[PDB]
Amino acid sequence: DIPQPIRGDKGATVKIPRNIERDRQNPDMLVPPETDHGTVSNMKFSFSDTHNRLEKGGYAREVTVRELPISENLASVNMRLKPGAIRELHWHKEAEWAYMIYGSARVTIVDEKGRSFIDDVGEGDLWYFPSGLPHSIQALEEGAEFLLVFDDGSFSANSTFQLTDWLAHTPKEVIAANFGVTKEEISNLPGKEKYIFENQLPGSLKDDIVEGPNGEVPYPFTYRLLEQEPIESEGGKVYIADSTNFKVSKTIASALVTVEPGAMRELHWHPNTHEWQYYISGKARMTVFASDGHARTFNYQAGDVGYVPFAMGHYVENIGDEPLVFLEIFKDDHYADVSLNQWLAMLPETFVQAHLDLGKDFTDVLSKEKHPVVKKK
Amino acid sequence: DIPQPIRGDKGATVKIPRNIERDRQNPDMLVPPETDHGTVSNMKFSFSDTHNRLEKGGYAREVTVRELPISENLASVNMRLKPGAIRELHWHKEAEWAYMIYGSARVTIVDEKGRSFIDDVGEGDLWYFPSGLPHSIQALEEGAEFLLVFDDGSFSANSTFQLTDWLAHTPKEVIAANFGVTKEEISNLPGKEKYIFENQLPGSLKDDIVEGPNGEVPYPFTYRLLEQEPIESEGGKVYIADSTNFKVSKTIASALVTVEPGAMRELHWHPNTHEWQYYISGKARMTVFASDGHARTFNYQAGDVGYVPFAMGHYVENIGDEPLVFLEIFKDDHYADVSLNQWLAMLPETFVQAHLDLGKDFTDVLSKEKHPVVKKK
Amino acid sequence: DIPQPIRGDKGATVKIPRNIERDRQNPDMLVPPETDHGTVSNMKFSFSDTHNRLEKGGYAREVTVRELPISENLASVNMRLKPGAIRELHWHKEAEWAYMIYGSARVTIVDEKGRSFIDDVGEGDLWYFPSGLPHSIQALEEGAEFLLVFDDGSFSANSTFQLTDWLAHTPKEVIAANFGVTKEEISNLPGKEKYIFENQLPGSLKDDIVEGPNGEVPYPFTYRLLEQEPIESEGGKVYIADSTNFKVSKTIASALVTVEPGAMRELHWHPNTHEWQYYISGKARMTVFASDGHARTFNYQAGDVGYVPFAMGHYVENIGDEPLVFLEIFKDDHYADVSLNQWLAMLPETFVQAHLDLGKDFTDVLSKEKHPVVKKK
Amino acid sequence: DIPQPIRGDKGATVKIPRNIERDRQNPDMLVPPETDHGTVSNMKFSFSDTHNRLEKGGYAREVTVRELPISENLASVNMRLKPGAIRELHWHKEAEWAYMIYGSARVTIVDEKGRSFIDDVGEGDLWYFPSGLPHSIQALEEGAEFLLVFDDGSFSANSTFQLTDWLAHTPKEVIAANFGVTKEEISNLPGKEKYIFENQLPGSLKDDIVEGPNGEVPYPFTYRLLEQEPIESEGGKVYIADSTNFKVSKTIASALVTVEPGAMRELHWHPNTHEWQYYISGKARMTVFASDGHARTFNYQAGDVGYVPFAMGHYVENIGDEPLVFLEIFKDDHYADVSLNQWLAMLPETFVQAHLDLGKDFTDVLSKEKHPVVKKK
Amino acid sequence: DIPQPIRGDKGATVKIPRNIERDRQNPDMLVPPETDHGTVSNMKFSFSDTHNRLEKGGYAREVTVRELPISENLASVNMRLKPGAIRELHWHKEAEWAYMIYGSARVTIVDEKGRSFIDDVGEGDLWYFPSGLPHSIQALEEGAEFLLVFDDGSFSANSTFQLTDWLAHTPKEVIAANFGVTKEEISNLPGKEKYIFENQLPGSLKDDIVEGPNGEVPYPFTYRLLEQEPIESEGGKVYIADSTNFKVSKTIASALVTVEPGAMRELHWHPNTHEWQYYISGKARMTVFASDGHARTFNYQAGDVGYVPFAMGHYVENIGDEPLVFLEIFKDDHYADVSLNQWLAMLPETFVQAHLDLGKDFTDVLSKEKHPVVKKK
Ligand SMILES: [Mn+2]
Ligand SMILES: [Mn+2]
Ligand SMILES: [Mn+2]
Ligand SMILES: [Mn+2]
Ligand SMILES: [Mn+2]
Ligand SMILES: [Mn+2]
Ligand SMILES: [Mn+2]
Ligand SMILES: [Mn+2]
Ligand SMILES: [Mn+2]
Ligand SMILES: [Mn+2]
């Protein structure tokens, strides 16, 4: 059918040409809850609405502050590599956190004492590369498709510092001198960046491991997120990875959230910092409570970016018949939330009653245990 | 079918959950021209991706700098009124330009010498309300749906200054004193804004015309755009309304562009200022040339906002089988463009040849007459 | 009498209409020391010059960056609660530090592991609520009046996140779902914020203490400042509370300063950060030394806010016949000062002499012990 | 010899490694007047201290806000073309003003009604291209070397919009469609920008003049500055070109100043806007008086950029044995100055005397006629 | 001879008046490597191009953000004191790091617990004064000339807080009261700042050491940099002083680099922060690789400031026949670099080969040990 922006005796049929397919994806935007109110910034953007850079070996498309201006501190890239294909050795100012959605890949990273780390990363796995440290990605036999997040929203995928591009812009005599070789021994250096390129599949991980005079790195740069025990509640699971368990991940705290059909991520806020969200699969709606009686509801599905400014109240409700699976990202060294339910459960009942104009029948239902994901009764 | 981001030997199939319906709307973004290159800001946003404020009498939804950060100087509202329904008497800092897409409506405006203007506005008609001057909209028997543009991108639809809201926040004794009445004579004033409200259809326009001690206003605030003679070229028409013909419209210059199937708005730029675009109907693609070998192609359809930063090169190509109809908006007192074709036509042939590495066979085809819309041969 | 801005052979009688009562409160501004010089920003603002929000149960009035633009990092609220009256359960981005001037009150706070803290706070007592953690205030039998300070000067008292306002702007079905109740079981929720409301006096503190599965909080959120041993000098006392003794108070370091008639807070500066001041009682004058031979003298009394930009030199001299009692606030994890006297006492005498063009008779008087408050001989 | 920063009993010999050649070029910086005082921003930069872009056909090197941060509104390029060599047809946001120091060149410009202007420019000649209008430069038989100024200090020489670069980044099918040609008819378009390129000398100017349906342009874009009558004073000449005589030059007002050995540009200020300076030949010193008893003296010679913030007092003294020849540039529609001498000449003598503590013997020497350049007696 | 900006078939002879002496100092700027490309900010400024403040006892000249706008976080002063001459007791917001190039000097510093530190500093020695703590410099028998660096680029040498200036702007009655003396006992205080003043040589360091009730300071404020063991590589030495060895130096990490004729500081970047450079002696060239195929080469010699924005690639090549000696400064608590050579040495050879299109003959030459300075073979 054809949705109309009508709610009871409010609204009207659309009369100008329109985008029906988008209206259908945004039922809570075309027809908001009556409890929404006031101007709130846009907190929703689709990777489908971005230009896709296509290379031999895959593609990369980004959502930045230039697309979603609210998110000044965090930007993201959806990257894809075909089997064996290489993301060129490179570096950047920003720290890089990543979630492997499809496939498997090998990463390399050398730190500032010249200690190397090389490791294979599967679906549900993370990596974190501290600011400025050089790294690579090479997909294995299935290829790889993954979400990268960078701790500056000004990030630009096109402006990474790359091995070949650096050498292509360094005088040949300096390069020769740096390495102790002749200009002729290096005449075949690429004249421009590679960025992403087809390459033969590598061998087994163990034959790549590079021994060095400098030691093993003190903390791993990868993390098996889905191998951890999750917080289980009635309608879903939550896997948390931050600087307290994923030790190198100093500037990025993360959670993977699974919400079953008919369940929701409960009403909570984050007392530490802004939340950046990516919707891996499923269909959701969320309301951002902005104080001063301002609130606005957004709809999300696979490939959408969401955002919740520091301390604003929210929930994320699965509104489809498949599991809702999304990531919660924070630029901080820990994950923290305050749950509406737990908060009220931990105060005197008559006090809460004074506040809400409700009785024992309500405060009796409060739970002092925190359940990040609840099921509808 | 299912589009893939593959172009020849570049790109790959998508392997993560995705938004197929959006991919289908963005063929030139999922699969960009090979001539696209480098980071360019987002220049595309859909009104379907915005929260819709529903009231008794219609609705309003906005696209601002909070949604499309590139457009710092211009914001827009898509507003809808049911028959007789009123947009409350109000005012704002920003100047207001409007295009009536569907229906008809009556506007009132009183200027700063207390001269009133009241007029009925049909499809294809414009209005312009200078900054700070108070105004209203009331839809006639068909209702009305129209596009408003404001000469500040920070504009917020919720923060207009409204008659009732002003009085609701003024001490009752001051109101009584201002008017020479008793507090009791005014006890029935609304306690909160109305914004949009159902009201009975008005009578004929001539019975509303208010006589005054102060004179007729010197220039009308409305304009019959589609009654003007358009620039006719081979594949379309262009109606221009700016401060030189629509005299009050000092801060906003506009063009309505119709592009036939298989035609395009030619390659041009604007030498004066940024272009803000609204796509009324049809399907388009445009490439923004950003200098330094940067360029990026965007797709648009009904309900989309587009933007072209000051002086960047572009074209707008109809890529559907219906007419493409869009508006070109500029915050300036005139419309100006420089056409690639005309520009080269007006230089010596051997000079142009020196530049493009092409011969008489090319420069022979150049036209010294400007044709804003061309047909494919 | 009638003060005139005349100092010896400088200045003149005022000849236009004037505000004599303010002139009398500002003797050192109408007639500055001859040693003052150059443009210095305003460092003085009165809570009496602010709009007072009146509610059933008390009032709140604020001094922010919108009032005192120099203070970009710190803002303050003077709040008042009648007996039993409640400051609605709420939260904010900013950390909250407070001094209880009059009365007593009960506070609640739940942290992010769902551990609650509930405690009664008397005159001379502090609290500190870390950013984002939810809290309440309820006055006991005497009522309560207290000074709140927030670690962002952009703070706005009207924009706190409140329990009822959040629920009033959340869809009723989501609320029902979050809690496992029916929409009817919650139909009585308030439709708008409460903010401050009359309520019956609570019972004894011990009957409120809420047991929980999560533990006692690791550090208390309140502090008995006046029960600490103060630094006693000849003309006054100084009580310091910062993150080293009041452990939770990470972002705010404080001092209460009592200065006897004829005494002054000595010449010092703060080597770490800006000083924000509140004048609880008494009458003072202070000179801010801004480098480059810039200096300006301000007058303060009860209800005034003062400020000293990072590292500028100053003193605070009691100029009335009652004790001067003011607070020194710093956005930092420690209190630090450098005393002019101690500094010079700790250098070679002939060196100091070389600097000041004075002899043994002066350097003999220097004290290597720090005396924050000195008496006139 | 070896200069030392010593002035009477102030200063000392330099004892660390140093740059003697620069010290010799900056006598008034290594050893400032005793009347200089306080922090003043840098107002001096050499084109010799910039990277020179070398192309086949010439070079271009720039001084921008990235080099001289004080000059936020104006930037400059020193460009050089070999005989016949072409500056690629291009455009920019900024308006372009130019002075032809060496050689001669042909310019083309097409305006926004498609009217072309083509003209030959000799030494002492100017051009002005309004923002956004496309243009070219081709040097004649002597080659050409000239100074360009742009009315935004953020200008970047590398980011101009160029004919070939635009086409290289436009889909071939769109180009074909725009022009009514086949993709094959245009397969030879350059793949990258040209920027500057060797080309055969053009023919006589009259064979290039392009006839058009649109008319002659209403005002010429070039100006014979040195053919105007200059203001002659005792020690030099001043040629003024601004929007009142060079009519198109709306955003840039200019003066060429010649100062004979032993003469100086008098003490004056500009009451309208900042002054940007280029030193064509000779050696100068200037003192910028910044108010609040701040002042600082700078040295300049050929290839130096200078700047004087809006309304600051100055003079420019030739300190070499050759003529001093420099340009005064203003982002404004007129040239204006206030002369210290004329100003005082036009007030009552006893008033001026009261001010300066001097007698008839001084005020008798004042001249009510303005003499921009004075000779030492 | 006379250098020309010609490189093979690119460039041309200069034809306008020019600054030949500067051209000679900038061979790589007048004639850049062909591998340079694109707009890069200025990273080069000479102290010779600054106004020199001359006082009785020495001089001070500064390079700030007002001179070198790229360096927003770090500014520097070149200061000179004659024998016995004093830098007035003073303080500032900024932390101060210093390198003693010529001579020897005594420093005093009193901390915020009133603990004093007094020490003599020779050539190759450092000091660090934490923000806000008061200090002095007095040169010994050879005089002293040294480089100061401040951890804010907005720093202004003229705006330090000075002992005498503070007292000159404090009411005499307050001063008398602060110290317990009479106004007459202090009538001889200086009326204005001293800043730098001639004074008799002090006595032996041990007779100055001031005993105090408060303890020895926990960490020294000076450091014997050249007495540490340096990193020795084939063509030079590197001495590192940061917060891990020079313990108080929390906000500034430093390295002294000596590069022999025919050697270079290798290709590396800093993964933590921007690099600020001072060239003590010798002649260098450096290329800054800015990503996106942007790079630009600068020339430096004694008295030059250089800068490398966070994470950009570079090398510093001695291009003269004397040792090149420069300082690397970072606003951070540690020194870190990533070496191109070590980085590649620590990855699989076939991987590096895949990247660079080179064979075993190249990867065989890589060194897993880091050699900051390499010699040409
Ligand atoms: Mn990366
Ligand atoms: Mn959340
Ligand atoms: Mn309006
Ligand atoms: Mn256009
Ligand atoms: Mn609070
Ligand atoms: Mn203080
Ligand atoms: Mn140009
Ligand atoms: Mn001037
Ligand atoms: Mn210092
Ligand atoms: Mn380095």
Image: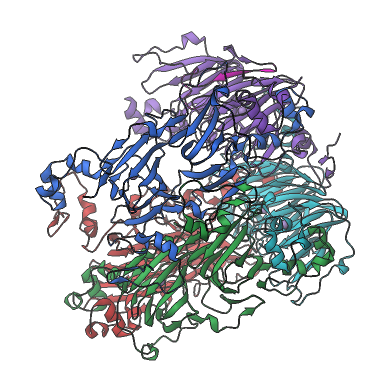
Chain colours: A cyan, B purple, C red, D blue, E green
Task: Identify the main secondary structure in magenta.
Answer: loop
Residue at horizontal 58 percent and vertical 73 percent from the top = E257
Does the segment drawn in magenta span residue B236?
yes
Image coords of residue E126 (percent x, y): 49, 78
Task: Using residue A264 as the reference point, say whether residue D213 is left or right of it.
Answer: left
Between E102 and D357, the residue placed more toward the observer is: E102
Q: Nearer the viewer, residue D258 or C374?
A: D258
Q: Position of residue E251 (x, y in %)?
A: 52, 70
Pinpoint residue C43: horizontal percent, then vertical percent: 34, 58
Q: How many marks?
A: 0
Rendering quarter of residue B355? top right
Q: Quadrant where the C terminus of chain C lies?
A: bottom left
The picture quadrant where one finds residue E320 is: bottom right
Q: Nearer the viewer, residue E320 or E86?
A: E320
Q: For this view, does D367 lie left or right of residue C266? A: left
Residue C298 in percent (x, y) is at: 28, 60
| E240 or A268: nearer the viewer | E240
The magenta stretch is B234-251
Q: Quadrant of the N terminus of chain C?
A: bottom left
Residue C117 shown left or right of residue E105 in the figure: right
Q: Is residue E110 visible?
A: yes
Looking at the rendering, the quadrant in which ligand 4 lies is top right
For residue E328, what is the image quadrant?
Answer: bottom right
